[PDB]
Amino acid sequence: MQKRAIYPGTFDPITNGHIDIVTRATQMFDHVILAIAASPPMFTLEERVALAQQATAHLGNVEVVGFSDLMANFARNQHATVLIRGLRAVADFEYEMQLAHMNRHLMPELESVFLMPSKEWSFISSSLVKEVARHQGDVTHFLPENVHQALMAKLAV
Amino acid sequence: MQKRAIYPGTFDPITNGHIDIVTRATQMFDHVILAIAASPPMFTLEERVALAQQATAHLGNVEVVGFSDLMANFARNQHATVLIRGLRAVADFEYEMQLAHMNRHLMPELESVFLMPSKEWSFISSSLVKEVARHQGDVTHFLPENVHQALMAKLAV
Amino acid sequence: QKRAIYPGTFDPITNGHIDIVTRATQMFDHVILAIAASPSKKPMFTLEERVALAQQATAHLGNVEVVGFSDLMANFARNQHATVLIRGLRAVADFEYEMQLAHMNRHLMPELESVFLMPSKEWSFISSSLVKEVARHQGDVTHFLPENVHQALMAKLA
Amino acid sequence: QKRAIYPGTFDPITNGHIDIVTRATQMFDHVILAIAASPSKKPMFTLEERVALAQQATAHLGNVEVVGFSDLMANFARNQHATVLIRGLRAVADFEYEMQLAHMNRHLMPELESVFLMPSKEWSFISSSLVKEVARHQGDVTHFLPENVHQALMAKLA
Amino acid sequence: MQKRAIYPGTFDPITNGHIDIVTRATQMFDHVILAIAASPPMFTLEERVALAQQATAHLGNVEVVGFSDLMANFARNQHATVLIRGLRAVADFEYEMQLAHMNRHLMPELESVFLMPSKEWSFISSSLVKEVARHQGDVTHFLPENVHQALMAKLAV
Amino acid sequence: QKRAIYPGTFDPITNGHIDIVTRATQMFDHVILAIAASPSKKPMFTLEERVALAQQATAHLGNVEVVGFSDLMANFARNQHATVLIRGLRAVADFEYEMQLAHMNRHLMPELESVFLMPSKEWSFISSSLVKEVARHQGDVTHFLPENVHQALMAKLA
Ligand SMILES: COc1nnc(-c2ccc(Cl)cc2)c(C)c1C
Ligand SMILES: COc1nnc(-c2ccc(Cl)cc2)c(C)c1C
Ligand SMILES: COc1nnc(-c2ccc(Cl)cc2)c(C)c1C
Ligand SMILES: [K+]
Ligand SMILES: [K+]
Ligand SMILES: [K+]
Ligand SMILES: [K+]
Ligand SMILES: [K+]
Ligand SMILES: [K+]
């Protein structure tokens, strides 16, 4: 089988945790669409797409695309049959169950798969990283270099 | 005993999960007040009351009423001794424990009872249903027909 | 007459169980405190001992009936003409197991409605297992057990 | 050819397990349903019995291979040339244990990628243990098991 | 060792749960800084500092101070080596793990310690107390007397 | 002199336990690593073996004292003149049990203050049980155990 998978999120900004997950996905499926949600917001959609493209340029079977529809609607149109979700902690799990049962109702031919990040990134999030950086904390370790540079520029002005 | 129970919520809108819970409550207690909170908001309070009355019209011992006070204050005034809460997942449980211990402090003669919805509705919520419908997803399966029609009208304008 | 069943292993019955069954009697006309034989749990007290301890500890509640059973709980509930199934909800961890049991029981007997009650803060962190563990090491558990149960626990461990 | 392994004790295999392995076969070219001997769990069925039950229950799935093992799971996965490790995610409580196992397995075999699938709502509240418990008390578990497994469970308990 | 510990929070307002935690901390460490975050808001920072000072005046090794930097940045500057966190329920625990691993990245010489409040305060929060009081519920039992008086005055106007 | 007790079964002591006790020694003047006999858990190593393994594994920490006990933990803590009770907090699931134990211990000895420390991310997904399970199947657990403990575990299983 030549599986097409979608890895959706806001990626605001994309972190080393996201890179970890999408890297694992590319080792599992023939084509991975890194789908950036237009809504919800430190970086614009065009900023978030460019940062994610640069940070995944080394992965040959990743396609970075923006989308504004319901995720399932975009997945259906893209002929994806696998929905990548990253699993960090118990707290996300309940919402992930809700979301996956809803997504299965909306598009039963799209199978949710949950990947586990490395221990290194199992306790971070885009939200926590932004909050720390906005309040003068060091987040260099959690971001690709291009994202780190864009984040510093964003927080300076 | 002729128990009076209250089933409070925002019911914005009332879903098949709420219908499930209140139906179970009516099989257990002589009178069930479906109490619609005035605050927090897709449908107005008058819209939410009308939709809930229509969706529960077949249940002879349900009374749909709006309220704006602290839930416990309204329950006390209504001479309710049972407080119906619907239990979906672990994530709600911690807040439910908080809320029930607070409600027991405010009105010790009001006993919180937790009912379990059917597996069919154990992974939905008014919030998730609204979000999906607002973003062009199909939520017909989760709502009474009158609510489905009102929701489509609401999202069209 | 609304009839509710409160099943459990009750090995032994604690003040947390007394809390839950008391709340149940304020809500329903008749409450059957149903003690499961639970051989797989290797209970410290025999079923006969646990029934006697619960009968004594609930004698002050006029609408409680203590019965032992080895049947399928759902069959025992139907045979007791119960339409309400009482379970106490203490912590996040048992909530998940309670939902499994309740969905299974609903498959076995859909007209038996599971209801969960919340114990007082006083008993929200104890369990039969924890009290037994403290007592095995001679720690004071008078605060967590009815008087007759405490005596019996002391005697059993002596 | 992408090869995935779905390991577990499968004592016995339930409709929830059939759900997960079916989803796996729609995603990966070949799925090894790997049954751990699990002596520490004192399984109701022998490994041979559990393999035979799973073979019959998955015969309709052309790309499932049922094998028993007593090895370290990670070594068995490497020796099956698997690069995907399937686990089903039912409730919040096992999620934590699943992460421990997956992080350990990643230490043992980093190229074996753990993936978690979510069963249908129908089977999200059952388990081999719960079905066995109901059946020990003669409750009807036909709905939760493949036909051959139900027969075998009835026979074993008779 | 003569340990300096920091107990940070918004304390809006300080509750009997906070008093419980800080009292336990003072029995464990030589000096406890009760650090009040300037950001996020019923009482102003100056109101929250004054209420906390009055409510902890009986504790001789407590110092109430406001701060506006990243907590770890303030802890570093204060030469704190212990970070007091109060642990109520499972729901907070996941965020507490996130926060503590981030704080350990930001300042590894600051050790997070988790204290457990009494059962009496294990189901309350500043947020729940404010919400109940704003909606005409009795919260006298959860607050120091000075905080109760200030809260009534605040809600009257 | 602030005295803290770090009780546990330590069967065997892991790098996660070493992490927690090290953090404790940086916070308190004297730390008693207290090994519970825990017969109900059927430990792999005797109490004497577990004390010897922990003594060797903590010899580099000058303010750690390793002692075995079969008493009620709270009584042992009082008799060690401890006023701080160290527990490590790994996952969501044990958090609930830890609160039960801590509230019970506070009832038994209110001046013993429970404190929870968080291990490094490196050890946040292991346990004595998991390491033993991997080792029973000959998987490599060198990374998770002190050298003397790894040797002893290999020898015991051989
Ligand atoms: C099935 O649940 C959902 N699936 N997708 C989305 C969604 C994602 C991205 C974008 Cl741009 C638009 C909509 C939402 C909001 C929900 C609740
Ligand atoms: C005891 O906790 C509570 N109980 N009731 C309410 C409440 C519900 C509905 C309405 Cl209209 C007003 C107030 C709130 C906000 C809280 C925190
Ligand atoms: C390491 O995580 C954090 N640590 N400290 C703070 C913080 C607290 C109080 C104040 Cl005034 C400013 C910043 C925040 C927002 C985060 C996410
Ligand atoms: K019990
Ligand atoms: K209980
Ligand atoms: K299994
Ligand atoms: K499963
Ligand atoms: K241990
Ligand atoms: K630990």
Image (cartoon, coloured by chain):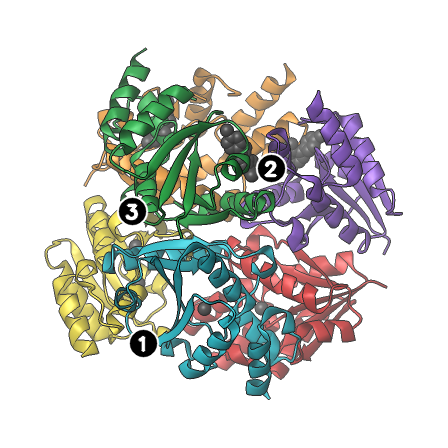
Chain colours: A green, B purple, C red, D cyan, E orange, F yellow
Can residue F157 be seen? yes
Q: Are marks 3 and 2 in contact (CB under 8 Å)?
A: no
Q: Which mark is residue B128?
A: 2
Decide: is E51 above or below E95: above
Residue B14 image position (x, y, % from top left): 73, 38
Task: Provide the residue designation for mark 1.
Answer: D70
User: Which one is nearer the viewer's eye here, C25 or A62?
Assistant: A62
**Residue drawn 39% across the image and 20% down it:** A46
Q: Is mark 1 within 8 Å of ligand 6?
A: no
The quarter of the picture showing ligand 9:
bottom left
What is the secondary structure assignment of the residue under circle 1? Answer: loop
Q: Amino acid at mark 3?
A: Lys
Looking at the rendered structure, whether the residues under marks 1 and 3 are on a common chain is answered as no
Q: Amino acid at mark 1?
A: Ser
- The quadrant holding residue F102 is bottom left
What is the secondary structure assignment of the residue under circle 3? Answer: helix
Image mark 2: chain: B
Label 3 to label 2: alpha-carbon separation: 30 Å
Label 1 to label 3: alpha-carbon separation: 28 Å
Q: Which mark is residue A119?
A: 3
Q: Is residue A26 left or right of residue B74?
A: left
Nearer the observer: mark 1 or 3; the answer is 1
Outermost residue, bottom side: D158
Q: Amino acid at mark 2?
A: Leu
